[PDB]
Amino acid sequence: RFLKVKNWETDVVLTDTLHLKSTLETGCTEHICMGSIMLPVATKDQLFPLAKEFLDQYYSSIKRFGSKAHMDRLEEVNKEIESTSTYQLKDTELIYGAKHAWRNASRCVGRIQWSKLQVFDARDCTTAHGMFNYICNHVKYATNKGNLRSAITIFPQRTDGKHDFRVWNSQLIRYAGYKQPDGSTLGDPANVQFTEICIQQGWKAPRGRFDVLPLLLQANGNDPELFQIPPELVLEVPIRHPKFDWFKDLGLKWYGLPAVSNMLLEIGGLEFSACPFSGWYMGTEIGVRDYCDNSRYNILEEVAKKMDLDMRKTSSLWKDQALVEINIAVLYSFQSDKVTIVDHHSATESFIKHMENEYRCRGGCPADWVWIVPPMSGSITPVFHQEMLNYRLTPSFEYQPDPWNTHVWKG
Amino acid sequence: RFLKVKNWETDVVLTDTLHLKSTLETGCTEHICMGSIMLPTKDQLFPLAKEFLDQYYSSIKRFGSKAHMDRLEEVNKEIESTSTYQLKDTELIYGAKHAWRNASRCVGRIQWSKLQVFDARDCTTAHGMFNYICNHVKYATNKGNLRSAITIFPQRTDGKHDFRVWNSQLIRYAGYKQPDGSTLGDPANVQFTEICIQQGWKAPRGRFDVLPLLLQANGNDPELFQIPPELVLEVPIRHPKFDWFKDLGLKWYGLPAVSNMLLEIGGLEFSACPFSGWYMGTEIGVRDYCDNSRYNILEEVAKKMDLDMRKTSSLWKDQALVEINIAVLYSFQSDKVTIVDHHSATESFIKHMENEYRCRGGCPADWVWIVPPMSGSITPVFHQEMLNYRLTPSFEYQPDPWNTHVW
Ligand code: HEM
Ligand code: HEM
Ligand SMILES: Cc1cc(N)nc(C[C@@H]2CNC[C@@H]2NCCNCCc2cccc(F)c2)c1
Ligand SMILES: Cc1cc(N)nc(C[C@@H]2CNC[C@@H]2NCCNCCc2cccc(F)c2)c1
Ligand SMILES: C[C@H](O)[C@H](O)[C@H]1CNc2nc(N)[nH]c(=O)c2N1
Ligand SMILES: C[C@H](O)[C@H](O)[C@H]1CNc2nc(N)[nH]c(=O)c2N1
Ligand SMILES: [Zn+2]
């Protein structure tokens, strides 16, 4: 079976065969498409086949499929599963696995970079304090004084599911949110609930608009513990506009390191429930989503007021006007401070090249159009006109529910 | 069975039950999602007819009544004896309004029940098709106070007697390949424009040349017709602040009128069914003007605005884009020609979805198409989960006839 995808701007047609290697379900059926739905303990029985598929992939990629090394490794994993109901990855398999989970991440526009990924093996970690230290080192390494470097830190795998390592923060660096009694919110409304948990756990809240949250870390299924990231490690950028001098007076800033900490990395059947990873920002993540979502900092009106736009009718496109200026400001501010950032035009152009390379070398590239197309100026980016096929490959990153919903409190 | 859709901005959760009444295949499977692919007998006909008549009689609260059963027998008999059947006028109007209501890619469906239907099933020639189409254009345009309309020509028979409009829309601009290699006018219509000349259209060879109609009646070779210019309402494009904008020499037509789709009602196939409503501003300002394979005017507008065109990160493309779209909306509004902006259209669609969930049990919607091609996440549709599924009656895309036909 072959499937074709077309670019409607260029007429370049591509052929997908990689999707034949897919096993997991998308959420779609022959009768319903779920492409815009955000969210559409294992047995030996299921485990050895998952390990095998993975190691066959790995040995093919080093071009030792069917080698003595390959066969000895399968036998050795089989024996470890038999004896212990699980197994441990070699360092090389871990590195390969984490890189491929990124390569396979269909919602990620940044995947041209997939093979340059610094992997930090934290599988010897045992306590929350140890987690905190590994996470500090990740942040310092990744930040690299503004010359951002991609990285991931991988804590011990799931065992019985009663002993999970988790980072309770959804990203390593995020700002507190405080719901006021009048119903307004100070800071980031997305973090209100997490901020409340932090506070209950003992965090002393500065109660400002941009307070960096503490880390909340759970080792070995234990109750999570609070740590403050040293401020000298948190790189931040004050937001100003190249032409509008009143922009700085809005008091906006943002952190330089986007570092997703709430996902589950699955490799050869093993589940890494704490695997924080980081890259660098595409500008629209901050300037469109974080600043301009109604449910977030919501600065559109205030910026439009200062621009003296006609705010009486939507058809003045005052929201669209303010939006571009804010995104100009974010790119200008990061660039002037020499902090790595990518605009949506450049990032999408690179993804198209990545995607075409992947069809040629790999036989495909799973991609989720709904997520890949930027949240402003969609159709003036090349990805808008690119047909894409979405399917699920492993190794993979997966969403997990927030731990406060699942955690058994020990006290 | 029951499926939920969440709005991530408002937290509102809706339950879909309408999808269980779905019949056609989406293109997706459990292993692969094809949500972004643009194109993913007597025995066959009676269940189709029955499925349709059951829903029709249910809608007028006469399900299982004598009139219902009688009609189902009359349609059975007609199929058994003729190999097809004929819709009552009431059924035709119901079917058309519902094909629009079921159109998952259409953001403007809040309007679905206000559709003027022109029954052209008595038409026999291309000259007659031209008359029907002229009347549709004049009725729909209404001197700028646009009204939604569809004109329905005779249904498919044995297949070699199809009625077809060859144009993809009733009103579009010519495209010509030029001596230097570049393109004059609309590059999307270069192929169609050459066929017009091939069949003998004397092309004025300008930028905004309204194309002639090419009409295929009863399976015959198509014929050329120029729409009376006085029936084609056009809008000169100016900017409310930029004096220089008028000087780019831009105009667009007021009436968007899709003419290449197939209407399917109760298993009957209406291959020529041009319909029209009114524009959302981004269709013109983002897609027609700014697509690279289209009029591609971003480069020139950014120049007039003396923006920094050195780096993509200056967002010069984005700044120009907004101003262009301000201009489209301004020109239409100043000339009293119906238009809707993307903010207003998407707000209305959310309101429609919620009406449809509560009144019908769902609303099929294709997020990829409903989200505007600019400013996506500042419109409410961006944050709205949608379920896409295929209900009949429906509109379906059909391939260009100049591949199918033999002269
Ligand atoms: C190197 C710079 C990178 C850029 C510019 C980039 C860009 C993006 C963007 C724009 C998204 C959509 C995210 C959103 O809108 O919330 C995304 C999603 C995602 N990225 Fe990348 N990314 C980068 C690096 C990485 C790395 C290093 C990994 C892991 C090794 C990764 C894995 C993922 C995953 C798993 C998602 C889906 C997130 C979710 O479901 O919430 N990305 N990326
Ligand atoms: C009254 C105002 C209307 C508005 C604002 C509107 C808006 C839109 C928009 C923005 C699209 C996306 C298609 C594109 O971007 O090319 C669309 C598609 C569509 N519309 Fe509506 N529409 C209106 C009336 C109608 C009517 C009267 C019908 C049929 C009776 C209709 C049926 C469809 C269909 C079948 C599509 C998908 C087209 C395709 O596959 O190329 N629309 N509409
Ligand atoms: C419900 C749900 C499901 C899901 N899969 N996900 C979410 C997080 C949402 C996705 N969209 C906004 C928020 N995500 C927040 C930040 N995502 C940054 C991705 C990124 C960028 C650059 C470098 C990197 F390493 C990583 C929620
Ligand atoms: C390949 C293919 C498939 C398909 N289904 N379709 C197409 C036409 C493309 C889609 N999108 C841009 C262009 N269609 C151009 C304009 N479509 C107008 C929709 C509309 C608006 C207001 C009132 C109406 F009555 C109708 C191509
Ligand atoms: C409902 C819809 O799927 C949801 O709003 C999605 C749309 N596209 C997205 N795309 C990205 N990159 N990030 C997101 O959070 C979303 N949200
Ligand atoms: C490849 C992709 O499906 C294609 O470019 C789509 C994207 N969304 C669209 N949305 C609308 N309304 N109209 C279109 O023509 C398209 N084109
Ligand atoms: Zn799908």
Image (cartoon, coloured by chain):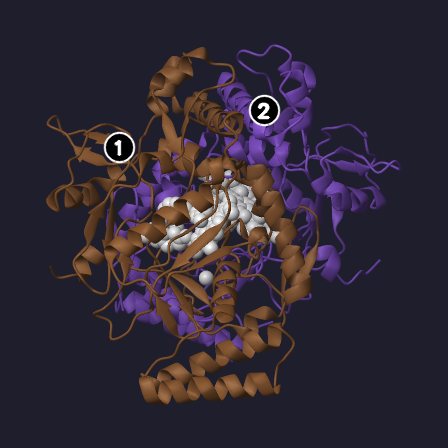
Chain colours: A purple, B brown
Q: Secondary structure at mark 1?
A: loop
- Label 1 packing within 10 angstroms: few (<14), some (14-19), many (20+): some
Q: Looking at the image, can residue B1 be seen?
A: no
Eyeballing the image, is B93 above or below A236? below
Q: Nearer the viewer, residue A227 or A329?
A: A329
Give the residue drawn at x 37%, y 38%.
B231
Give the residue drawn at x 48%, y 82%.
B50
User: What is the chain identity of the residue bearing mark 1?
Assistant: B
- Label 2 packing within 10 angstroms: few (<14), some (14-19), many (20+): many
User: Left of A363 or right of it: where is A165?
Assistant: right
Q: Secondary structure at mark 2?
A: helix
Residue B43 locus on image (x, y percent): 35, 87
Q: Which residue is mark 2?
A: A322
Mark 2 CB in 8 Å range of ligand 1? Answer: no
Residue A316 locus on image (x, y percent): 58, 26
Q: Amino acid at mark 2?
A: Ala
Q: Are marks 2 and 1 on the same chain?
A: no
Locate residue A271: give its quadrant.
bottom right
Residue B344 locus on image (x, y percent): 60, 39
Q: Which mark is residue B209?
A: 1
Q: Amino acid at mark 1?
A: Asp
Q: Nearer the viewer, residue A90 or A95?
A: A95
